Image (tube, coloured by chain):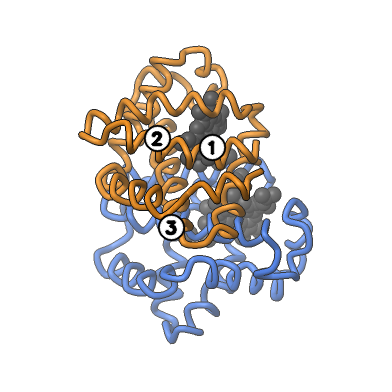
Chain colours: A blue, B orange
Amino acid sequence: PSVYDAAAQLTADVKKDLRDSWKVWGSDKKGNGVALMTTLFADNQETIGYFKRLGDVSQGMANDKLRGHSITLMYALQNFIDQLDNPDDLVCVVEKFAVNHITRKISAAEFGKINGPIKKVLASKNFGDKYANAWAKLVAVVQAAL
Amino acid sequence: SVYDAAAQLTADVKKDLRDSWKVWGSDKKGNGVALMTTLFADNQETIGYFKRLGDVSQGMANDKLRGHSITLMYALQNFIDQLDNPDDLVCVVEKFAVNHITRKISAAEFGKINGPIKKVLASKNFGDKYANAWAKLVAVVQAAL
Ligand code: HEM
Ligand code: HEM
Ligand SMILES: [Xe]
Ligand SMILES: [Xe]
Ligand SMILES: [Xe]
Ligand SMILES: [Xe]
């Protein structure tokens, strides 16, 4: 299967659930981006070494490099959400960010580690399993490129 | 100083940035690709840096260029959204500065984007006042390079 295949398979219902949840947990990109990363490092401590450029990622909001990273990650997600209705456009931005991760030797399975943290941050805003599953389908579009 | 450069974004400059972005940022694919092709056409000595993207003369038809160009416009979106808070603007500017330092882009070469910005804004009826505002934002990145 192709990335385009994965992008084309996102249905109206999945896109609605992505948009509805993103309206909330994408609204505070600094706060929720840093929370997402902090949750990744709490539950997947084996990934911390990949992020050495950011310095001490336990410093959370106080760490300027972590904050800048985290905000920018949330604009990658903003970009994806805004491209949902045009698979051509979604694929080309997914492929861009996939290259960012391939050059860091991040596998499809490793990228998929983000689903745990997304599920938790969603649940902190009372978006439950249906929303986590929708986000896993979007994550899987990136995995198709990895 | 990146912090001193950020301090140049006064109330009037922030307003001009926001007012012009409401138009410029409303079509990120079309306007992003137009900005890039203007850069390449008018500054051909920069094209070599973009080798990953392949044949950039293909413009919109080049998938890698399209993905790059959309994403660039979300960097600008990010900057606009940080204008309220100099500390946050600086940390995202520094992030993107690192991206350009790895590509061996200097402050002077980054500043080559100002001609293209002036041109594409003028075509949308945002003139020198708006170009100058965007130049002040570009200068924040330049200070970090
Ligand atoms: C929702 C999921 C994710 C998104 C949207 C995302 C997005 C990003 C973005 C936008 C960057 C900056 C790229 C650059 O400037 O070169 C980045 C960097 C990075 N990402 Fe992710 N990422 C995600 C998940 C992950 C996961 C789960 C891992 C690892 C297991 C990972 C590892 C990395 C690494 C190592 C970097 C480089 C950090 C640095 O040195 O600047 N990413 N990511
Ligand atoms: C408004 C001004 C600009 C902004 C906001 C901007 C933004 C970006 C962004 C967001 C990326 C992706 C970074 C990554 O994923 O590693 C990037 C890549 C790049 N930028 Fe810029 N950029 C600007 C101007 C310039 C200029 C003027 C030059 C060169 C003279 C330049 C050279 C590059 C290069 C060579 C890449 C890497 C392309 C690739 O191989 O993927 N940038 N830029
Ligand atoms: Xe990504
Ligand atoms: Xe994603
Ligand atoms: Xe930038
Ligand atoms: Xe900029």
Q: Say left or right for B73 vs A71.
A: left
Question: Which amino acid, mark 2?
Answer: Asn
User: Which SS class for mark 3?
Assistant: helix
Percent of width and height locating residue B19: 28, 49
Say few, some or many: other residues with alpha carbon within 10 Å of mark 3 (under 14 / 14 to 19 / 20 or more): some
Say few, some or many: other residues with alpha carbon within 10 Å of mark 2 (under 14 / 14 to 19 / 20 or more): some
Question: Which amino acid, mark 3?
Answer: Asp
Quadrant hosting residue A71 = bottom right
Residue B120 badge = none
The residue most toward the left is: B125
Tag count in the figure? Answer: 3
Residue B81 badge = 3
Quadrant hosting residue B108 = top right
Percent of width and height locating residue B15: 34, 52
Q: Which residue is mark 1?
A: B139
Percent of width and height locating residue A73: 53, 57
Subunit under mark 3 = B
User: In the rendered view, would you say B38 is above or below B82?
Assistant: above
Instruction: Give the alpha-carbon distance from disc 1 to disc 3, as whole Å.
Output: 17 Å
